[PDB]
Image (cartoon, rainbow, N blue to C red; front, side, top):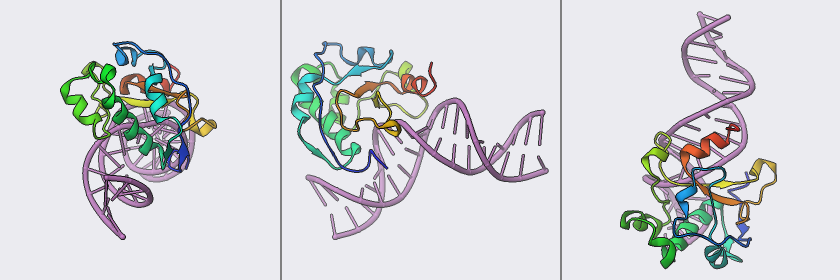
Length: 132
DNA sequence: GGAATTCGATCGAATTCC
DNA sequence: GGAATTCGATCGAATTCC
């Protein structure tokens, strides 16, 4: 459908902490680092999947951000895989951080609109798809 | 009725193919 | 390498089965 067809990176991003994802299990998670929003902005993406792997790959290229992550998780982001969330933050076999579109795609949501993109935990992500 | 399999929105990772 | 395709996953409302 939509997150599969190509698109263009757009958005400002937000200024971020040294404890970024630290609050990814609350409300709508952690925003997309402006520092990263700058790097990805105006880039062409085949699918959201393409954007995701590129996204985490930029995080690993960031001194400030990649330092907050374990050597292990950095190894995964270097190849496009998402970071591993804290156990108390996982939901079944879903264990990697998830990117949530604030305004659903099935409701005309910017697929590649970094201002509509956020980082969450599987646990929290689920409570979002049911109002809680 | 009420338990069981499906469906369809939302996800990330592995495999296939050129 | 990179793109497309395919496989796994959790959940609630929905449909299918006795």
